[PDB]
Image (cartoon, rainbow, N blue to C red; front, side, top):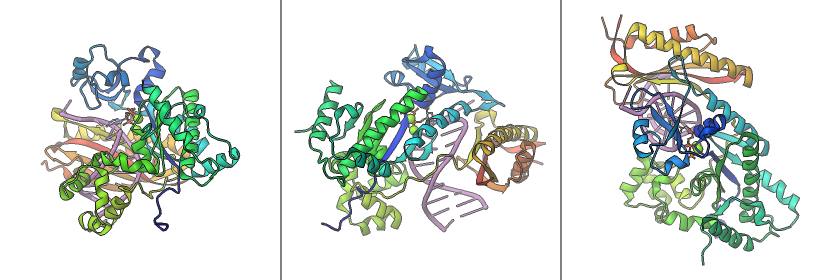
Length: 425
DNA sequence: ATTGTGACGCT
DNA sequence: AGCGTCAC
Ligand SMILES: Nc1ncnc2c1ncn2[C@H]1C[C@H](O)[C@@H](COP(=O)(O)OP(=O)(O)OP(=O)(O)O)O1
Ligand SMILES: [Mg+2]
Ligand SMILES: [Mg+2]
């Protein structure tokens, strides 16, 4: 009743750049704009692996993780942009720098949590209070929400429907109550329209967004209407939305835990979780997961938007599949050196930009014929930004995996160097 | 022969 | 610390 808190205390947004690597390449090369086009890494094995897909190309069935030769079978006019290769490996610097452009603009409006290269959460609670008291009571015009969908409306042409739903929502709004969560979400959506407009004006990049009361709902909302649109998921919309929502669509339930929720409880949709007690869920999935599930099937989640605009780790990884697996000492050293040289470049730039130094080096490998993505992960001290030293140290830390009696056995199918444990500098 | 990331939990 | 999960 009155004492049942409803998870309506915050306004949270999730902003995701539409097919981001594709947009970066389309800005750089206007011949690629408004076309079926994809970004690919490498080119020799089956045309390269596709890692990003424009919405025009998705309409033909082109997806990430597809070989370019196969995507061309589905879409013969598919245009391709290749990731840069440096020191023998893909180098994602152009996309990291484009991401910083976008994150820096987002940070003008509110505090952000960089979730990935192309996604950030936004804590809009204080921004909305400021904008509300600036309003001083006047209603919110549909004109301020030109690309917003209100999930679940209308009830009782796509753009026509969008506007019908938005009118129904705005007519219902009690503007005089500055504490109404629905009003707070709406003002959040206004600010996110402004944020997205600034991003597109100042970078050329388009993005979609979700606006709700917590991170999981905002991310779910963001997926509902892409590309170049934003979706408001109100607390009231959760029962109908979750009633037919596959459990795997909720963030963190797309993997083995989600599968076990489905298998153990014999359900399919998020809303079905409401039938279980908190203790029942904890008994199946542990104290933390159980409490989290109990609240989240009711629309409630308390994970904070962390004030963190920069990555916590700086990593350099390469897979060596098939007959390209590394089999000699010289080979393992030369690739460790290539990785360490890219890492040194990125670390020196990071220290200059962001006033910090990494203090720990993580070295991870995969051996041929191991079924894990990671076979071993050991750390050592990272004391200076020297590629020769970092590569010698990573070797020193992995060398006792060689079981040869100049040769390397078993052959290595992945190398990975990660700088971690930053401290202010 | 999805790759190259990057965040977080468990013990 | 080292390993595992999750989401791209
Ligand atoms: N599995 C992956 N491997 C490599 N790069 C990836 C992978 N997933 C995503 N990326 C990169 C390329 C994408 O442009 C960028 C953002 O990923 P993501 O947001 O899932 O898709 P997207 O931005 O390409 O399209 P969407 O419009 O659906 O968001 O990160
Ligand atoms: Mg995206
Ligand atoms: Mg994303």
